[PDB]
Amino acid sequence: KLAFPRELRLLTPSQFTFVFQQPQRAGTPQITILGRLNSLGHPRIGLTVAKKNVRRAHERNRIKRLTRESFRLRQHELPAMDFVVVAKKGVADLDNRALSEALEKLWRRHCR
RNA sequence: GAAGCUGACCAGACAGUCGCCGCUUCGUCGUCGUCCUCUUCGGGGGAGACGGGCGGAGGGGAGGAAAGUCCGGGCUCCAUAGGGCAGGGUGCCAGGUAACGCCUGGGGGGGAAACCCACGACCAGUGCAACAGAGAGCAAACCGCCGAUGGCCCGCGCAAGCGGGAUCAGGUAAGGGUGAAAGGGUGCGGUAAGAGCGCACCGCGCGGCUGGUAACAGUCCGUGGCACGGUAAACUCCACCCGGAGCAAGGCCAAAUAGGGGUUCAUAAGGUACGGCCCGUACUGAACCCGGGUAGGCUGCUUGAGCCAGUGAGCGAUUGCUGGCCUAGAUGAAUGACUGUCCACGACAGAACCCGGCUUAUCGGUCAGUUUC
Ligand SMILES: [Ca+2]
Ligand SMILES: [Ca+2]
Ligand SMILES: [Ca+2]
Ligand SMILES: [Ca+2]
Ligand SMILES: [Ca+2]
Ligand SMILES: [Ca+2]
Ligand SMILES: [Ca+2]
Image (tube, rainbow, N blue to C red; front, side, top):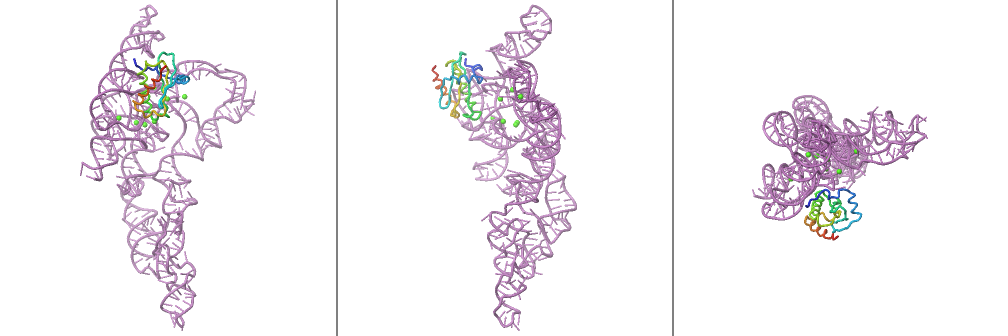
């Protein structure tokens, strides 16, 4: 299966703080990923995109929609991490293809 | 058939699989902590709630601006002798509406480029221009004013007929005159070259009078020979109205240490609400010592001062009847990919308790009007 259940989301601020204490890190000039190993036996993810880097609400929502997808469509191929994903200033004009071509070569860095 | 502009609908459609979030409903599970029947005390359809209780199945899910921080209103909690003061708003006339700083029709501004109106007071001081004397109306008559208008000047012969003087700005005032900006026109022996200065006909006042719902309007009847220019997005007055906060408002069900004193003020203090500020006016209340909880869930929540259709009333804004009708509500916070046709080859952009306006953003269509090729 390739569902994306509530159980797979970092729902609370403490869960963000934990991965920031000990992150393994990968990122481009525009987009970046942090993660720590976890005991739950499957991956998890949490999103934050700064209103400072990406203005107007139709944008940001696009970056959520596309990045939530590229996680669940790869769910079984990376270790049982807890992950955080954050947008730098330079993302807000990349087309849907231009995020998706990057997130693959970004996850190709996670040789752990 | 040649350019805009106003109004309309719209700014994408359908099919495949891979998913996200609620709705409805069927059995599934716990539980009975309702009890129908009350039993076998299982809990049976359980009478009944709720949780993945759990699996189906059906049927749904971003605006005309959802943007803004701007005006009006609901709802809820809180505050409230109020007599002043302070501080914001709104200022032709009628109507609409639940209310507005919104809408409609009229009046007056221009009712055209007024296809546009911050449409009460112009005096209570002050600033007209920068520059005037044109600075509020101030007054250099600018060429006159000598115009013999006066004096008196003196030269004409005593001059009395002729020139000058400007005398005293010189009947001016703004007759007339360049210089800016200007307190009535245009005429008439306007008389010394002259003016409401007299006298026509117009202004313009102020009072009648006829229209109007009323702003207002009419040479329609008297009129003063007549008496603020302009400007309050100018400081001024004048009239009327103005109490906080936010859906994590608020409940309800929970969950809990409320423990010498206090700031021994007494007495009442001075604390704080009235209240920005004073005047009362109310309440009395102890700078904390002797302080932990809750940090949850349910509800408020999507039915709207709504929509549609048929028929009355109205110049319009709107609105009276009589039939119907309704699956965004999330809570790290709910919409991707492949394909083949539209070109409009797809702009600006998004919900957060809800309803009425206004403002701002916006590739481009296709219609209907309406001024133009
Ligand atoms: Ca649309
Ligand atoms: Ca808003
Ligand atoms: Ca509260
Ligand atoms: Ca709610
Ligand atoms: Ca919130
Ligand atoms: Ca509305
Ligand atoms: Ca509204």
